[PDB]
Image: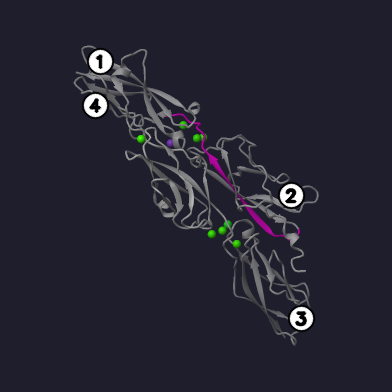
Amino acid sequence: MQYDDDWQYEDCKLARGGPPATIVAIDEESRNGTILVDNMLIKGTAGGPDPTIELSLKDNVDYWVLLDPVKQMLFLNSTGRVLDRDPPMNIHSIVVQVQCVNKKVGTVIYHEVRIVVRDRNDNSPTFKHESYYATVNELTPVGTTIFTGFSGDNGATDIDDGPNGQIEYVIQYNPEDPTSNDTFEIPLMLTGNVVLRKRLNYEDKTRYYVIIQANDRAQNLNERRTTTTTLTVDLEH
Amino acid sequence: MQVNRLPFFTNHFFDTYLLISEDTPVGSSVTQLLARDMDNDPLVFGVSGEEASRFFAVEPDTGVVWLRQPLDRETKSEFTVEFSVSDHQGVITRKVNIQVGGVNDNAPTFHNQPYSVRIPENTPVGTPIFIVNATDPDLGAGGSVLYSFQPPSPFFAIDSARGIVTVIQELDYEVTQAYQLTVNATDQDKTRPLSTLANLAIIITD
Ligand SMILES: [Ca+2]
Ligand SMILES: [Ca+2]
Ligand SMILES: [Ca+2]
Ligand SMILES: [Ca+2]
Ligand SMILES: [Ca+2]
Ligand SMILES: [Ca+2]
Ligand SMILES: [Ca+2]
Ligand SMILES: [Cl-]
Ligand SMILES: [K+]
């Protein structure tokens, strides 16, 4: 006879095995109405004309989450805004509780939902300045580093996380100054420091327009983003 | 001459999270770091930073990650750890979000003990006379408390969800002057429920 009534306590318990927290990942900047959890799998029926449970959200900071109690589904609520993982918003995860009240015995169980927000490559490299400049003496030896102006966030930065936000620098051929990519080199693409590759001649040529492109390091080559600047190099006598 | 190209991690958990159950035994492998190097350089792996070096260790030649001390979801539900990989010419690092998985590993703790109450012998049947409370920090069913008397009393009942104690049968001082009842607070974990006992003294007056 003891524990004959334990069926009364079943509603509000998980209708699945596995760990108590429900953990999902969703892309940053997902559209309003995006499904966060397809089915909470909680035993019992919320809503309808004869519910055995009541379901509601607790600790729903900034109301990112919306609950449909009948389907036990959780959705993103982002109308008039965006779920942004990047600075300045910095939303890396959303944690909410699905409170379940068992109507028959009045017990309350909290089912935690942890939503990990994944970074998208939605930002391009941005240069701090619109253009860059270097002055080099004509007698500068070949192999000398002549520009280091991308050091310490003075060059291109990228607000995404991981390789999405890491930059590589490369010199491109300049059809309006064809010898510039032959006279200068960026041998270490991660720094974008520029080194002299050919001997200079002030009596021949006094200015170079070096086209430098910064790209991020997204895993998918077709999702990489690029930005271009010009380094103007002037000789001094 | 080819300049050195630094290694890069390939694990997909860096793009999301790595879930590790709090009941994972110390010494257990939790994952294996994977990396590539365009020079085909042999790679050496490590853990980097304070909180990482605390909980994890890394086999340097294989990248196997293992638990150096226990996790505890009740203390820390998630944290960020930085791993390193090196081709002996440069070291690169990358951070991963660790989500700590819950299991039922606490019993409930009672509030406001000791429990004692004096009631007159003519307290009517149905009268609520006391409220017991206990909390439990585990997630979900493992954190939801049920109260009972062990064994049940023919003179008092306790509401299983609310902890309210009521008189259910007429009292008689000359027969019984005091009751020492055991209250059980249990969580509702399916596989490993945990519980705690408290005494409740009910003193009957004149
Ligand atoms: Ca963004
Ligand atoms: Ca980017
Ligand atoms: Ca991003
Ligand atoms: Ca290498
Ligand atoms: Ca624990
Ligand atoms: Ca626990
Ligand atoms: Ca517990
Ligand atoms: Cl837990
Ligand atoms: K970045």
Instruction: Say which chain tag 1 marks.
Output: A
Q: CA distance from mark 1 to mark 2?
A: 79 Å
Quickly name the residue at label 3. Answer: B171
Asked whether disc 1 touches disc 2, contact meaning CB atoms under 8 Å apart, the reply is no
Kindly identify the amino acid type of the residue bearing the numbered disc 1: Thr
Vertical relation: A102 (above or below) A227:
below
Vertical relation: A177 (above or below) A55:
above
Q: Relative to the observer, which residue lies in front, A211 or B54?
A: B54
Crowd class of label 3 (few under 14; some 14 to 19; many from 20; radius 10 Å): many
Residue A46: assigned label:
2
Task: Tell me the SS state at disc 2.
Answer: loop
Kindly identify the amino acid type of the residue bearing the numbered disc 4: Thr
In this rendering, the label closer to the viewer, 3 or 4: 4
Q: Are marks 1 and 2 on the same chain?
A: yes
Q: Position of residue B102 (x, y in %)?
A: 57, 55
Whether residue A124 is in magenta: the answer is: yes
Q: Position of residue A102 (x, y in %)?
A: 72, 57
Quickly name the residue at label 1. Answer: A206
Vertical relation: A18 (above or below) B205:
above
Q: Which residues are magenta?
A: A104-125
| Image side of residue B84 versus residue A146, left or right | right
Earlier in the chain: of badge 1 and badge 4, it is 4
Kindly identify the amino acid type of the residue bearing the numbered disc 2: Ala
Quickly name the residue at label 4. Answer: A144
Q: Quadrant of residue B143?
A: bottom right
Instruction: Say which chain tag 3 marks.
Output: B
